[PDB]
Image 1 (cartoon, each protein chain N blue to C red):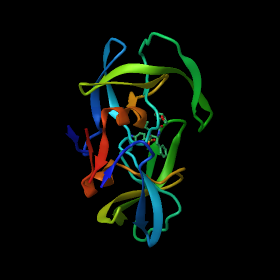
Image 2: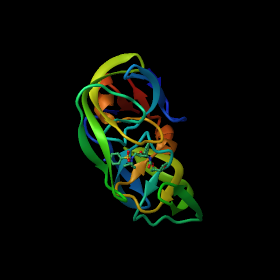
Image 3: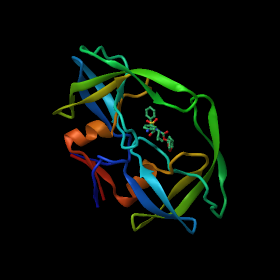
Image 4: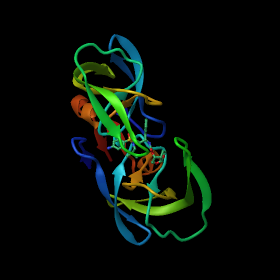
Length: 99
Length: 99
Ligand SMILES: CC(C)CN(C[C@@H](O)[C@H](Cc1ccccc1)NC(=O)O[C@H]1CO[C@H]2OCC[C@H]21)S(=O)(=O)c1ccc(N)cc1
């Protein structure tokens, strides 16, 4: 699809057996969800760094569906006001900026 | 141009008689630069909101050149680690997300 940027680019996600929404965020290196229950192994990751750090759970090679596009990528799980699809997963669906 | 997202989407900016770089950030509503000296009238704006607020100077209808595209939009001036082009100016250059 072609998504214009007059509104926040919020899209429908299937992740961890749940239906979610997330923001397409070209300013974020990483993808972060809260309130998902992912199976499999994880490792702790410190992210952020301003004010302190936040400790999140890093899950590798997570199957995820973004706008009907079934892809795989690293997902961080921790507190976030709006779930965020970062560049690490936008590359997987083939998403570019165009003008 | 078509910009892929394997790297941070940092582009060349002409603003306030200066050459700058800024990140194309679809997760940001607003555009924020530091260390620019913009002419004209401004008004205070509170942005952020997490940890406290940050007070910035809001300048309306600022002429700015983004990748050789000469456009106009609101620019906030305050502290930021990397200058940020938000949706308010990506719409002006006709930038979309595509996949
Ligand atoms: C400015 C970014 C570097 C900050 N981040 C995302 C950012 O886009 C959030 C988006 C966002 C979404 C969910 C959770 C946190 C942050 N919005 C934002 O701060 O935009 C500001 C710049 O212009 C202004 O206009 C509106 C807000 C102002 S960030 O996700 O925390 C981030 C910071 C550093 C890295 N390496 C990777 C990601």
